[PDB]
Image (cartoon, rainbow, N blue to C red; front, side, top):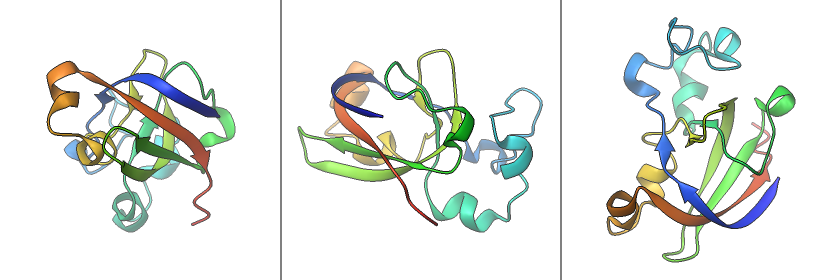
Length: 125
């Protein structure tokens, strides 16, 4: 749940693509079947993270809490929303929410990875 100095990768999957209708065959995220059906409001209100990695194993009773993300190097920090869990080593199904916001002066893009700190946080929506 609490990992620091993480040599993080940047696999930011692309939600928006299909208005978050994850139900769409080829995608099907953990809560897709339940969440894809929520009116655009909540869905877009916050960002989006189908989460993955090594530390922070939270799949089952996870689709309800948030993941806080900070970049010590620049000071950039945001609150993420744990929606799904992947098994191939990504990070999040962002594209526009965490990386795309806490990206630095291109470092992240120039390398394909960065060093961050993330802690599980409850957003109690």
